[PDB]
Each structure stands twice: as structure tokens, then as C-alpha cells.
Length: 359
Image 1 (tube, helix red, strand yellow):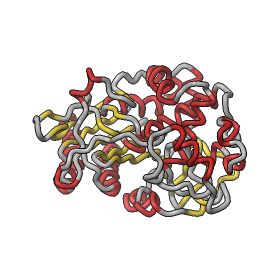
Image 2: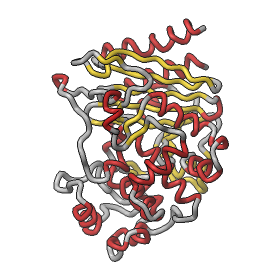
Image 3: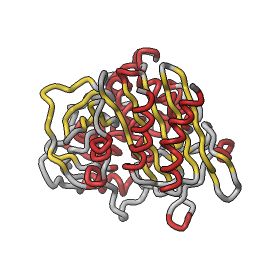
């Protein structure tokens, strides 16, 4: 039974770790309100430190689900509305094209072609980021094409923080992580916890821990353990267990605004019908989905992302590859954290084998 679950997770993980040369991988599963942890290999190859459920990994774009939760809190406090013009929350943007762009457009990558990343010319500097947004002009009409963009959801989180009158990083550390009960979740890893921070590995096992970048906190800033990220998944599965404004914050991340192919776009979370084929879930998490613009099919009203659906988010940095998925209607949650950036198709392959086997 524990033997069966170990066999299922081992069968899904071991070949993918071997095929993708992944030094270390942490799995956490929430099954009928019980946590299960499976830890593989090395957090650091050089000093032989083993992965545990307390090992910290970079989760990259999975950070956007925390950014969406902070925005959900600002929405619950009536400090902002998704149909607000972006420039409402930052006077520096008054007179810019952000006068004509909604917070919802920023959150769902439909602002009109904000790029995948800030150009190399924009450094982690308040004035450079300000001047970048002031000069930016859309390629196409806001609300028409999805282009996955760090500057887009970055500005969404930055503006959500301005609506609450405090810096983004302060709000996350002082309000969001404590409200969610997350003590092993960091934007800036304390010196005392550095022993838990896994090494990331790239080409020729070059060591890679994420360096500073513009709106890094909002887009890809979070370092967390498999155990902490599963607590976050369990909060998402049962928002009603939190104090009401935080319950409302998490619910705001479970609302679908439009479809691209099989995927329904929420704030942070991306949803699929469940069941669905592995090939379809791989295609929804494919490189073209990340790198190319897609015409959206807008929903007449926002859809509740609950019941027979899989909510998921991939996230990467140069050295790390994360995947989180949950099935609201089955009280099933999954976290897969690795210290190599391995293909999304392979992350989805592990998840699919586990989620299929638990069913």
C-alpha cells in the first residue's frame, strides 16, 4: 500500500531522472488530505547533500501563482479591480499606453505583446523599469492575443502591491506567506536556511542559482520546499479553511477568463478538463504555447476552475524545473521540484503517471 504508492512514484520518476540527468528531485503528493513525500538524489553533487522534503528549490514561473494570490488579496480588500486601467495604480504610467490596458490584460498576458522577458538593456533598477513601461507600445489590441510575458504578470504584481501601499517583497514575506502557513518559502533565502538551498545545474553541470532581474520577485522569485509548496496546493484545494479574505484571495486564482486550445487561463493557474490525454496536457505546456502569440477564445462570463479539471503551472530558471498540479474535484495535489531545467513534456509525463495511478 505504501509499497504500491512508492512503486507508482518510483516508476514515474526514476526513468525521467535518468533520461534528463536530473541530480535531485522532490515529489510531494496530497491524497485524501494526507501528505506523501518522495525524495530522490542530490541537492548538491559536490558536497553529497541529499534531497529531502525541506530542500529549497527555485520554482521559477510557479511564483506567478503566489503573485496571483497577493492580487486576490488586493481584490478581496477592494484596493483594486481587474477592470482597472494599469496607470490607475502608478502615476509614472499616466499618459502612457497603460492608460488603455486593464489589470486583467496584464495578469492573463493579453496586454498587446509585452515580450517573454525584459530586454537585456533593462536592469533591476526602479527607474529603468519605469522608463521601459512608459515608452512601451502594443503590437496588437489589448485583450486579443495571449503572449506569455514576465513584464506582463510582473507589472500586474507590482501594481497589486502599489494598490496595498507596500513593496511587493514586504507584502509577500510579512502577509502572504504567514497567512498561508509557509515558513520554508522565501523570495530572499535567509543565511540560516542557505544549507537547504539546492544547487541548480545547466550545461556541463555548470552551477546556476537565479541572479537579480527586473520584477524577479513577481515573475520567478520564490524558493520553496516540496513540503511548503504542497501546503500551498492544500490551501488551493481547501481555501475555506483559511481566514475569509485569504479564502477569497485563493478563490480569485480559480477563475478562467479565456481558452487557448485545451487550456483555460486563470490568474497564475492554467486549467484543463480532467481526464485528458497526456499528449494534450503536454501540448498545452509546450514551447509554442510559451513562445508564440495565440488568439484567445474569451468566455462570456469568468468560469469557476473546479470539479473535473486539472489546474497546473510549470516553472523554470536556468538551473531548476518545477511543476505543480491539482484536481479540485478529487482532493488530489502534486508537486515535482528538480534542480535541472528539464523539458515541460517530461515533467508532465511524471505527473500524468502519478495522477493516473492515484485514480
